[PDB]
Image (cartoon, one colour):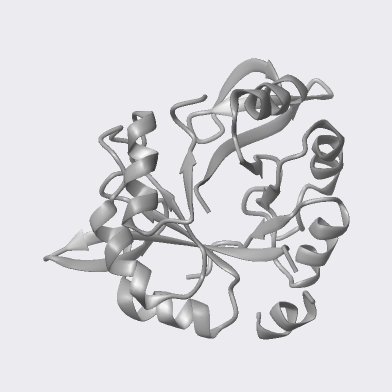
Amino acid sequence: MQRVVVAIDAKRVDGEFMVFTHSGKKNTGILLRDWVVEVEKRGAGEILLTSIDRDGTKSGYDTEMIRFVRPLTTLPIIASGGAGKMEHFLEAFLAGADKALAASVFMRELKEYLKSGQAVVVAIDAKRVDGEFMVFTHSGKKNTGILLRDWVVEVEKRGAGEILLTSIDRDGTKSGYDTEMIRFVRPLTTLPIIASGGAGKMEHFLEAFLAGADAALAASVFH
């Protein structure tokens, strides 16, 4: 509820966990240790902690990084990058992550087992295509031909605990969240929705919550 989520991407550099920007390409020179605190103090309510070392590998989550960060923050940590098997969610949860972000999918048992507070987050990226909301994969480059409407429903049916809903249309713009898309999606799913793509002012978060978002992601207005 009104959760502000901050995306932190990190990677090992000379045996240190360094924070990266620009899709994990730019070494900011800031230590993961320092940023995680600064972010909490700055007022984040959740951390999406992406391991650039694991991101798309199937080898499992970066449990080392997760354990590294756990002592440093009180915030819920969503682990990201590396998932390939259901146990990995257990593996990440054991390491201290409060949630895990499922790998790019192009779950009903774990959902039942979690009894609460811990969830699997599923990323859905969508875009306007001929006035239709379509799911895209591949950083918004590939249309899947599946309607957002249908996929949100499917995802929930298949036992996801939460949806990370990225608007390819707003992502990178700093012009505000895709409130239209948020509103389209909201009645379709009972899952918490983390809105993503578009933040540019503190006022933009308010708009997303109003549009029906439970949490709002920003990778921009911090890093």
